[PDB]
Length: 298
Image 1 (cartoon, helix red, strand yellow):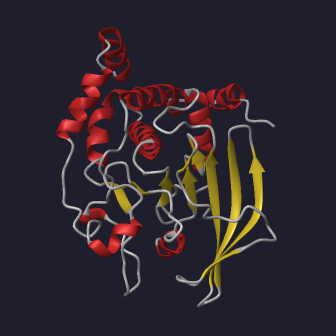
Image 2: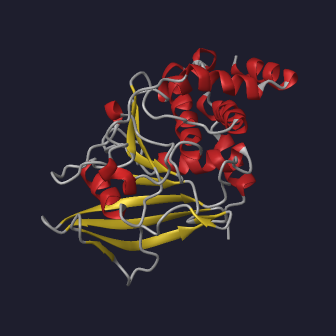
């Protein structure tokens, strides 16, 4: 039981050691493309790069590089694209990726400004009448509507390929109260948010991989994906005890480095999955409970 391990780790206060063990056992693959001189201004952080084997390639001849990784969870049967918060010069690239990968949703777990510093470019329109056009990738983005909650906002966007004039509806799920290098306010608010994303169909197999990002695309983004995958695995077998969170995390780290940046984010991941297990195992009412406990209204 993940709960037994949780109490065992909690009692001995060994989260730091457990987390460090994961870092030590984590995969290490080359990131040659990310490190090419020409891509220097396409990376937000020097120490966070996508592995060559799992990087998302832009469908363009000039330069197909973008700091984004495809996390393909074979057993769980779900894929996620984790990427860094778009830079002022990579916003066109970001939307090009969303278009080419056929993503239906974008999950943003950070705020544009955190700790008094800019962690992400304003890559989506904030006002309906002020659409955005990315000339480099020939894409147009328009805000259609938004639903603001106390700690998260859901926006309906229309992305248009100006070359073919084809358009697609993209859902933007913005978690606005998750501290950089921190954890959500409670498993409830986090789970409420995850299921909001799930209910939208953005994580569904009929669509391309959901795009998930924070500032570097590994900490909060990793926590989000780890929790989701663990719950999906548990759901497929209806066997909570069969899910090994640490092994799932190590599996995800074969696709992108540093997923889950702190021992506390790891601990939170356990909490989210344990609590989420109640819903998965048949207690549908718990979903309404999370919504209430999250106080999303206002």
